[PDB]
């Protein structure tokens, strides 16, 4: 316990000065996630109807 | 400037000074457990002598 608690706070000492540039670096990167993970999800749900029609392209014609 | 947890993107800090004449630029990377804070002699969290 004597050494375990102490380690976590002190090692962020040179990082202490760059507090302002990171809080705002973060926000805009999360705005970047808003579009980059919208476009990407949209590609998956479309495969939903493409494979559903591909299902009935094969299942109806393999039969005859 | 350290790299905590799962990390990739970090910028530089210091602005206000006169940039006279250089020779080159160099990067490097070391663990915080491997190398202690300089200017003491003995530190509690330095338990890696290798």
Image (cartoon, coloured by chain):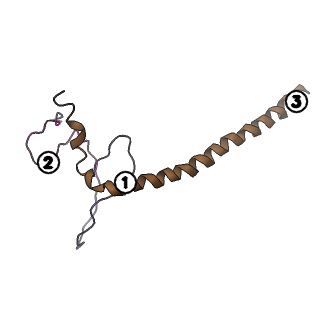
Identify which residue is drawn at 84% across, 28% down. A59
Tag of residue B30 = none
* Viewer-side residue, A28 vs B35: A28
Chain that is coloured brown in the picture: A
Mark 2 neighbour class, 10 Å CA radius: few under 14, some 14 to 19, many 20 or more: few
Give the secondary structure at mark 2: loop
Residue B4 x/y as whole percent: 32, 43
Q: Position of residue B11 (x, y in %)?
A: 35, 56
Say if labels 1 and 3 share a chain: yes
Choose between A19 and B25: the one closer to the eye: A19
Say which of A30 and B33 sits in front: A30
Residues at marks 2 and 1, common chain? no
User: Mark 1 = which residue?
Assistant: A22
Numbered-mark total: 3
At 9% from the left and 45% from the top, the residue drawn is B40
Frontmost of labels 2 and 1 is: 1
Q: Decide: is B35 above or below B26.
A: above
* Chain identifier for the purple-coloured part of the image: B
Q: On the rendered structure, is A64 left or right of A18?
A: right
Q: Chain of mark 1?
A: A
Most common secondary structure along the magenta stretch: loop
- Report which residue position mark 3 lands on: A60
Q: Is residue B47 left or right of residue A41?
A: left
Position in image of residue B32 (x %, y %): 24, 42
The residues tagged by marks 1 and 3 sit, at their Cα atoms, a distance apart of: 57 Å
Q: Over which residues does the magenta segment extend?
A: B26-50
């Amino acid at each position: 316990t004597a050494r375990g608690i102490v380690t976590d706070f002190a090692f962020l000492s040179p990082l202490a000065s760059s507090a302002a540039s990171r809080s705002s670096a973060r926000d805009d990167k999360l705005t970047a996630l808003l579009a980059q993970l919208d476009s990407l999800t949209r590609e998956l749900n479309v495969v939903s109807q493409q494979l559903l029609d591909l299902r009935q392209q094969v299942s109806a014609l393999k039969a005859s | 400037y350290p790299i905590p947890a799962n990390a990739t993107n970090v910028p530089i800090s210091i602005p206000s000074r006169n940039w006279a004449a250089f020779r080159g630029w160099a990067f490097t990377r070391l663990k915080t457990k491997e190398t202690p804070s300089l200017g003491s002699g003995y530190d509690p969290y330095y338990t890696y002598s290798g």
